[PDB]
Length: 184
Ligand SMILES: [Zn+2]
Image (cartoon, rainbow, N blue to C red):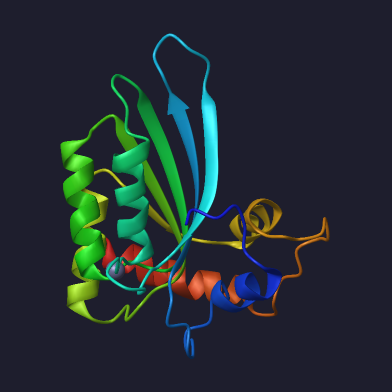
């Protein structure tokens, strides 16, 4: 953690965008990061975080990203454009922290593409997402193009083509409309 890639079956299993997702008990989070140091060309980082429950380093993937980012990456004077591609939308605790962080470090911008909405009808969860939309962060649902990109960048794909599951696009529309509605 951060790993450079997922296995194929972990990707197809954990990023499938069904409404009833049994039992994806982990969250996975791919990221790209455009590091804009100030008198230098742009550089890029790329990775994958899984949530942790070992000994005493419990973190949802979001916290691990943030702990890794602060401890090892955040630097004087440089700007950052982060993108996440996340299996599940964030719990409201995680969304809480992230929104703090953004408001506090305004040199960082954050886009979050999410494959699935955890409990989209519940307001504690809708709250998290509204909070993040407020502190700057874009929140989108992953569509076909985003799945293809993560396949091509975060998986040991053996150079094979992405193989979309049936229903991928339908699931995207259903979840998009739910997002639009939640973010009034
Ligand atoms: Zn969380």
